[PDB]
Length: 279
Image (cartoon, rainbow, N blue to C red; front, top):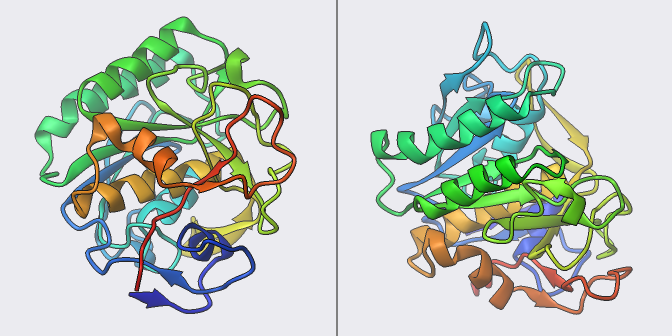
């Protein structure tokens, strides 16, 4: 399938080269796969989700995404226009309040929730979790991410927006999960993207256009927005049977675009998420 004039992020993950505007993907598009967006929640009623998005858990008075960042990330994973896996099922775990903040214990509860809820969901092609959140290092948050990955969900996490080594940020520093740095449309490391040996892949992270609350759209930047690209790519990859949740992040690293990114620190992988789709 070919989506013309797609967001540069989508076109980039289906491209050996930057500067293109058409997203190419197998029409299965993550059908039968699931992506938990652990964030501020999802505007499930947004027309871009086509009834494929749904809140499954909130730890606050409402499951409504009063922030938009979780709706944005869910849009990058599997919205119809803005999404990697345009047919995946999106599940909202609102662990972040509408200010975008969440206690680690709530974030840990949401991760253990997904590890169990996936057994309440129909994901024959595989389960993915996209955590566009992060704070200082927490060996408990890392273990919660390790558990979620251990349970049979891919864990895609943001490297963080600190222009630092992600070793000091959780769940970015958890080695078993998939830590995603951010890149811009010129294949530069997104200036804000965290780096380091713990990073597993880079995704489109700068000026990412996707869904927003109020049925709208907007373009915002972050490793928190490269992460849904990789989470959507994972669900896309599990649906084609090219990988499993336990082996998706490495797979994406194995099939990535190598050495194409600029300003990658010495010691950080120079890998860009690439769907390897050949029309």
